[PDB]
Image 1 (cartoon, rainbow over the protein chains, first blue to last red):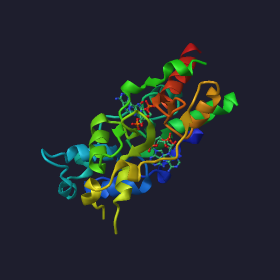
Image 2: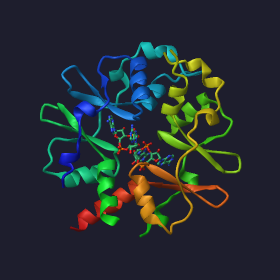
Image 3: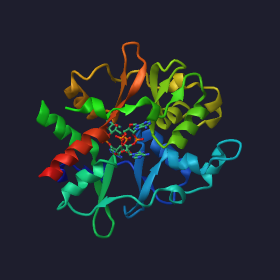
Image 4: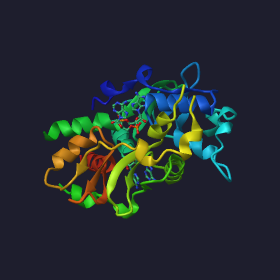
Amino acid sequence: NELADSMISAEKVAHVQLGNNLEHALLVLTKCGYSVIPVLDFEFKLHGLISAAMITDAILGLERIEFERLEDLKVEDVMQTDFPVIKDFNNNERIVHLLVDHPFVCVVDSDHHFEGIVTRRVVLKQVNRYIH
Amino acid sequence: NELADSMISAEKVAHVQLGNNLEHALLVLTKCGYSVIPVLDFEFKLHGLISAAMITDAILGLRIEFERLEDLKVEDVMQTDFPVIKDFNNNERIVHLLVDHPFVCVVDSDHHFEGIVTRRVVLKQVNRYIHLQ
Ligand SMILES: Nc1ncnc2c1ncn2[C@@H]1O[C@@H]2COP(=O)(O)O[C@H]3[C@@H](O)[C@H](n4cnc5c(N)ncnc54)O[C@@H]3COP(=O)(O)O[C@H]2[C@H]1O
Ligand SMILES: Nc1ncnc2c1ncn2[C@@H]1O[C@@H]2COP(=O)(O)O[C@H]3[C@@H](O)[C@H](n4cnc5c(N)ncnc54)O[C@@H]3COP(=O)(O)O[C@H]2[C@H]1O
C-alpha cells in the first residue's frame, strides 16, 4: 500500500562496514544517532544488525566494562544475524505484521543485496493522516 | 479508542535512578535490552529519558573517553525535554506523538510516572484491522 514508494533508500541509511572493529562501530552508531543499523560489506550485501547494546554486552568483564577490547573485536563477532527481511513488495501485509515487533525491516534482493529499509514511522505517518 | 487500557504499567518499565553514574546507566540499558528508558527519582517522579547514544555522545572527545563514565551522573546527560501524557482525553494527540516518539510516558499531576504508551500498541491495532479485511 505504497510502503514501497516510502522505503528509505539504502544510500540514506547509516550502516557499519563488515570487518570494522567495535570501536569504529560505536563511533558510527554515536554520530548517526540511530540505535540499530545494518552491517554491510564493500558490495553492500547485508550481513546483520548492530547496536551499542550488542557491543557493550560483548565487552562485559567480571569487574568492569572492558573497553580496551573494543579494538580487538570485529562487528561480525557481535552483530545480530537472525532478523526478518523483505525480498519483495507483493506481501506488504507481512511488512505491517513485521513492524509490530521490529522498528524497521531490511529489504533485499534475491542475492541478499541491501536495497533499503521500511520503518514504523512510515506507517504511523499514514495512520495519523487518516484520523486528522 | 482503547489506548488507556493498553498502557504498559510502570512496574514493567525498566528505568535508571537519579544520581547514578553513566556506567550504571549503561549496565541497565545493556541488561534490560531497551535502548531508551526513563529516569526516575526515589519518589517515582519522572525526570528524563536516557540512551547509550546520549551517554557516548557526552564523552566523545577529540576518540570516546570511557574513563569519565564514573564521574558523570545520568542527570548530566539525560534528555529533559520530552512530551508526556496527562490524560486520555486527547488520544489523537497520542497517535500524533508516536509518529516521532517510539513511546510517551504517562504521569499524574505531580509528575509521578505511571507507565508508557508505545508505538507497538498502535501497530497491533493496524495489523488487527488488516486481518479483518
Ligand atoms: N535522526 C533522526 N531524525 C528524525 N527522527 C529520528 C532520528 N533518529 C530517531 N528518530 C525517531 O526515533 C525513532 C527510533 O529510532 P531508532 O534509532 O531507535 O530506530 C530506528 C533506526 O534504528 C532505523 N532507522 C531509521 N532511519 C534510519 C537511517 N536513515 N539509517 C539507519 N537506520 C535507520 O529504524 C528504526 C525506526 O525508525 P523510525 O524513523 O520509525 O523511528 C525513529 C524516529 O521516529
Ligand atoms: N523484550 C522485548 N520483547 C518484545 N519486543 C521487544 C523487546 N525489546 C524490544 N522489542 C521490540 O523492539 C522495539 C524497539 O525497542 P526499543 O528498545 O528501541 O524502544 C522501546 C523502548 O525505548 C521503550 N520501551 C518499550 N517497552 C519498554 C520497557 N518495558 N521498559 C523500558 N522501555 C521500554 O519504548 C520503545 C518502543 O517499544 P515498542 O514495544 O513500541 O517497540 C519495541 C519492541 O516491539
